[PDB]
Each structure stands twice: as structure tokens, then as C-alpha cells.
Amino acid sequence: SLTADQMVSALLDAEPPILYSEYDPTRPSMMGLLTNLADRELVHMINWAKRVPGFVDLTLHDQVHLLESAWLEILMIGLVWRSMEHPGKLLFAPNLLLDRNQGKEGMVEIFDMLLATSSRFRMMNLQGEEFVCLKSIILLNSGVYTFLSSTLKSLEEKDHIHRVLDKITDTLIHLMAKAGLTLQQQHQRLAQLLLILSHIRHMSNKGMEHLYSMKSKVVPSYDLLLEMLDA
Amino acid sequence: SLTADQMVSALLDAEPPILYSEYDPTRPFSMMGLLTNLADRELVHMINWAKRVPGFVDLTLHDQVHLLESAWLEILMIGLVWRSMEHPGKLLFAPNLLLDRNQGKSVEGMVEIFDMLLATSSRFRMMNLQGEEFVCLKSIILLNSGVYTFLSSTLKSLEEKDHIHRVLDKITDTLIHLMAKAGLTLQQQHQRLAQLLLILSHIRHMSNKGMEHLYSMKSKNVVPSYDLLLEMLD
Ligand SMILES: CN(C)CCOc1ccc([C@H]2C[C@]3(C)[C@@H](O)CC[C@H]3[C@@H]3CCc4cc(O)ccc4[C@@H]32)cc1
Ligand SMILES: CN(C)CCOc1ccc([C@H]2C[C@]3(C)[C@@H](O)CC[C@H]3[C@@H]3CCc4cc(O)ccc4[C@@H]32)cc1
Ligand SMILES: [Mg+2]
Image (tube, rainbow over all chains, first blue to last red):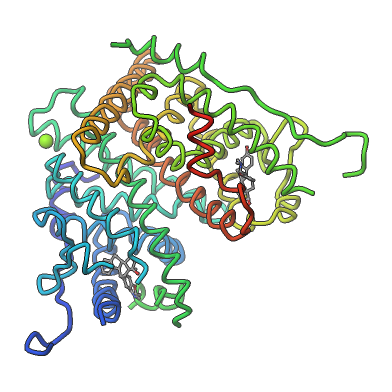
């Protein structure tokens, strides 16, 4: 029942904080810093996911499935968003801005992919309001095709998810109309934004490939995610 | 310069044929071998199709190879999902190779992917995806999949990226026009456009999982090389 303006207000209000890397800056490695940062960001991501309109209407199992599918894409879109005003570098945290040379485990290709994404956001002059919409779309869409369930409940859950996704589409279009874009510019920009999400999916897949290769007891389990969502 | 109708006409005409699996149907019924040979032959036709997608051959041959390298398995997959739409619970790899979920388990690499593909065809059916929309989506995959990974900012590459995005914009216009022709409201148009493009993220995911398996095989030419793709495009 939320208006487009109310949807934007809700998403802006739900935004998680920007966290810091944990290292003492007076002291003279990187994977441990990034892993600890991501570990702390995931806790705040669960809080954010619960404030995305329609997300807590789903079952806890479906909430876990969506977050299990989307968490690294959500970390990556956040990283790209905070790196937009840092050409050629990635702002993992305010105290951890790395260039491509510093990027050289698992980042041989991904670093450049992330840089290219932030470059594209810059080319498009992506707005904060648009960004939070995109991030919510990732949460709701990434796992919606892989519930592996044809129960009556699951059919209803998928319908709900797509209704909420439709509302966010309406909201994105509304933001563009507010800005004075023509109808043609509106549907072109909508398409351009959603097509970037495929690239973010690609980057997450490559990132998840590395995390699994580590064989470190480093990918959040279903049961960990379930514990956090119901806490 | 193409109009929306002309863009659709062009894409419909560029459509590759549906190929058959190569096995003797009188012999006892090898699945990965059959599927690989099928895909090998499909890829040859895919290159012909790609060259007929408006705007594609305007690109440098290097950039054409890069786009196809990025997109080819996605394109095979959306093709598969399209020709499986009217076969719930099954995948029509070829007209003489219709596999169900149980048979899917006989296929290495498909423990999760088979169900993912089925879910996509189910979603296409629920949306009543039209042929005109399908060819638009397939062209979008070709142009979009590799456009952020050129790893070049030569003046030429800047121009190539702009061109690609202008063509992508035209296909967006074309999709919206098809929906308007069908009498959808403006709200329904932008909702459906979004629904269609969001499925492309799932298709990328499936391709990445498929590519993971192909690389795991450590089989020469089971992933087409850059030079193989270049030889076919040229
Ligand atoms: C969350 N806990 C439960 C599990 C730890 O997950 C992690 C641990 C480390 C990262 C780092 C390290 C990588 C995966 C590299 O290898 C290849 C891509 C890297 C990503 C990039 C995205 C990203 C964004 C962030 O803002 C913080 C960390 C990271 C990552 C990302 C997620
Ligand atoms: C093209 N030549 C140069 C290289 C061979 O590429 C191949 C070889 C075999 C396939 C098969 C086997 C798989 C990858 C499984 O493993 C996991 C996903 C499978 C995909 C599914 C998509 C697909 C669609 C087709 O219409 C024909 C084959 C296939 C594939 C797909 C592509
Ligand atoms: Mg704008």
C-alpha cells in the first residue's frame, strides 16, 4: 500500500551504516581484514533486509533463501556505491581504500569488474534513491527462481515477491519522472540499471567460487543466517 | 536508424534453426557426449545469428569475440528454456532429445542447473513470453553480458561501449513498443520490461554454474577458445 515516495523513504531509512576495517592504523593480511569487515556487515545486512517493505511478510525459510542467494551481491553493490567518487580504487572501508595493484586472494579478475561497475554508476550519475531501490531488487529477485518448492505457500510467496518487485519498478520510474526524464528516457534508464544487476550477479558468482575454494568453515551457513534473521 | 518494427523483423529473420541430437534412434539409448556435440553445432549457427543482430558487426572483431565469449552459454540456455516452455517438467535439448528431471541426473554438471532451467521456463510460461520479446532478450544478452569487461579505455573502446549502449537502448524501445502494440498500460509496460530483464540475471547465474562445470572437465575445446571464436566470426 506504500506510495513511491513512502517506499523511497522506507529504504533510505533502512540503510545500514558504513563500517570500518579493524586494524590499528599506528601499526605497519588483507583477506583477513576484508573477511572480518564482511562478517560485521552481514549482521547489519540482516537488519536492513527486515526493513525492506514486504520482506518480513515472507516465511523465515524464504527470507533465509533470499539472503543466502543475495548476500555477496549486496556487499558488492554497496562497495561499488561507496567507491563511485574514487576512480580506479575500491573503498572497502573509509580506512581501507585499495587501488588495483593492492587488489592483486580471489580478486585477480573481480577487482577490475567492480571498478568497471563503479565507473558505470558514475557514467550514469546513479542517485542514492535509485541505489537503494536496486539493492532491494537484488534481495528480492536473486533467489526467487530457486525456492525448489511448489507448495501452495510457495506459490503465494513468489506472487508476493513479484508484487513487491513491481512496486519497486514503479518507484524507480517515479523517481525518474520526478527528475523530469521523458517516458523514453525513463524506460531506457530503468533497463540500463537492471542490466547492471546481471553483471553484479556475475561478480558474486566469481566471488562465491573463491570463498568455497578456501574450504574455511567463510560462507554463511543456512543455519547461521536463520539464527540471525530470527534473533 | 531502425524502427521498432524493423528491429523485430530483423531479429526474427536472424533466428538460428533448431538442431537435432546426433544419435541413431533405432539403437539402444552418453548424454554429455550428445549434449556437447549438439552445443558444438549450435555455436556455429550462433555466430551467424550474432552477425545479423543489428549493430553487432559495427563492432571491432575483437569486441565481437569478447561479447560472444561472455554470452554464448547464456544464449544456448535461453534458447533451451524457450523451446522447453510448452514441456512442463522437461527440457527439450533437441526435438529428439527431451529429458525429464530424472534423466537430468544422468548429466554431469546438472545437479542444480536442470531445476534452475525448468524454473526459468516455468516463469516464461507464467509471463506468457512472446517470440518477439524472446528475440529481443536474446540480443540483449549478446550485447550486455561482456560490455563491462572489455578491460580497455582506448578511445576506440569508449566509442564501442557507447555504440553498444545505444543499440541496447533501441532494443529497450523495441520491447516497450511490442508491449504498447499489445495494449498494455504504461505501468504494465515498465513492470513487464523489468520482469523480463530481471530473469536475465538468473540466466547469467545458470551460465556461470554451467561454465564452472565445463572448466572442471579439463577437456580441450569444451570451452570455445578466443581464437576459435575469432576464426568463426571472421
Ligand atoms: C560474511 N561472512 C560471514 C563471510 C565472509 O564473507 C566475505 C569475506 C571476504 C570478502 C571479500 C573478498 C572477496 C570475496 C575476494 O575473495 C573476491 C571478491 C572479494 C569480495 C568483494 C566484495 C566485498 C565487499 C565488501 O564490503 C567486503 C568484502 C568483499 C569481499 C567478501 C565476503
Ligand atoms: C560449444 N562447444 C564449443 C563447447 C561445448 O559446450 C557445451 C557442452 C555441453 C553443454 C550441455 C551440458 C551442460 C553444460 C551441463 O554440463 C551443465 C549445463 C548444461 C548445459 C545446458 C545448456 C545447454 C543448452 C543446449 O542447447 C545444449 C547443451 C547445453 C549444456 C553445453 C555447452
Ligand atoms: Mg536522472
